[PDB]
Length: 121
Image 1 (spheres, one colour):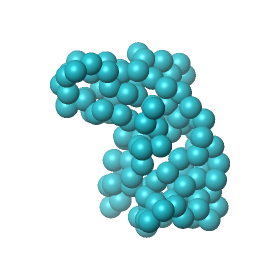
Image 2 (cartoon, helix red, strand yellow):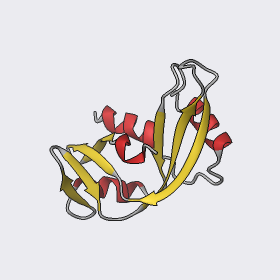
Image 3 (cartoon, one colour):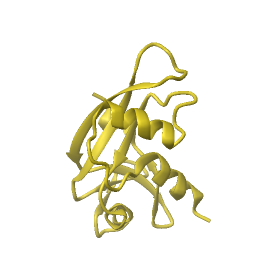
Image 4 (tube, one colour):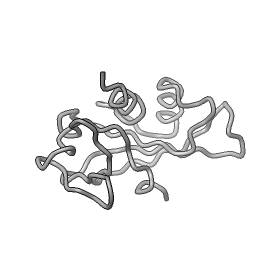
């Protein structure tokens, strides 16, 4: 029904990651099917699904710019940035762990888009 929310979880949610190093990013980017062609930058949010959904309402979200929402709470995140010249696999990634609020778009109370711009660096 809300398959864009499914896509969001697939691309942008990893509940309990462990060690969030380069080899983490390389494995998860492959497993979530984000490596043909290699996604240039991708952030996974960690922790509770409830907290993420809550960004779609006043509970854990504020309106942001045009059509976006921004979280009140800070999340543990890991950003996977592609390195090398090639857009095609194998896809080597550098991992950047973080802890901050996130920017999403919501539809019908569910996140369907992560704004990756805030993780570029």
